[PDB]
Amino acid sequence: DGKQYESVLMVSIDQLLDSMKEIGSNCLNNEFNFFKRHICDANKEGMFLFRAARKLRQFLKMNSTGDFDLHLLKVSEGTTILLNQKKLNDLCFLKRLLQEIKTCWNKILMGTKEH
Amino acid sequence: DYSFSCYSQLEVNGSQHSLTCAFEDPDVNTTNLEFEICGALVEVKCLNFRKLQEIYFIETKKFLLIGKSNICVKVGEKSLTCKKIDLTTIVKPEAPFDLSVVYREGANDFVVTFNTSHLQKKYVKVLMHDVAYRQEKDENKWTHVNLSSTKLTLLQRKLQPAAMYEIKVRSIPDHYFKGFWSEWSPSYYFRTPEI
Image (cartoon, rainbow over all chains, first blue to last red; front, side, top):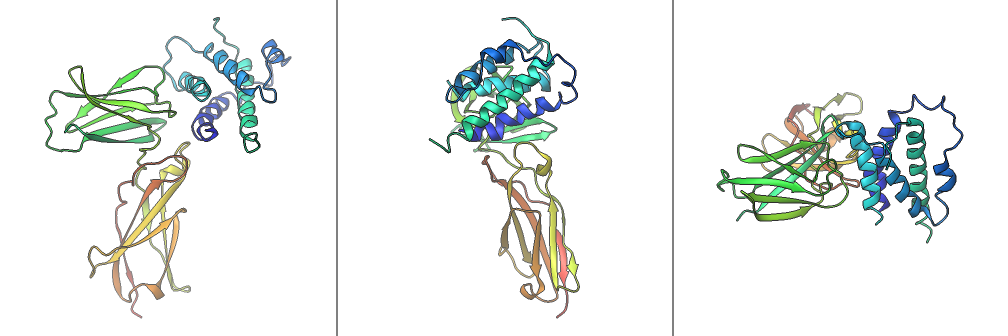
């Protein structure tokens, strides 16, 4: 079902990252604790995407009507369907979050043509 | 009885998608009937279609495009019938356009080319095109050609001399998505030289 990701889910992750390619080169990059505590480690990738998807919702504003929020919703409600708090505003963390989500999806993919 | 069929169109208006349904019996009484879709949506749980004469249709960006949805023909609030469709398998491409035949004097062949707005789309960007053509004198006997690119070449050697041909194209989803043939492109008419 990784075909689902590549063809539908990934379209949204990429669109989101595109609206954030201007940001980045300016925030204290010092990895956040989220990534220190949660890694998409070999055969434990599922646990990561799940959490990552959940963390994502925390960036949803009330008026969840806008290409941006819709893409966020699609990525996580979507990642969730393929497997089984406080509000945030830092786009640096979201940007890094999306990047790690893509990377994790890649391992799960270039890892089934294995088993 | 109340049977119906639908086709979705992704990124048909910008990044907005559209789902369109209609009863198969064109004479069915639709002045009390309602169409609704639930599941595989995002901000909301279900969506209410909009009747536009005999057909019902939705235009949104709220389709998840992962998993089946439940379209129902409601009568007031009674679910007369429902089907579970996966909006990614009933896609109908937009019709190709800017068809254009060009005769190359030297190579004694015609180079047919066309365009499809699907190229710059993000989802349904892989299509299987069907180029169809026939000769005026002939009827209902078209020569089809399946292409995957937007350029096709016919040889004069294979086309009747001094004749008027009618040619047209249409596309169908071909990679991850599934669906139906798009409407035909407008026809183009060209004449083959006198051999």
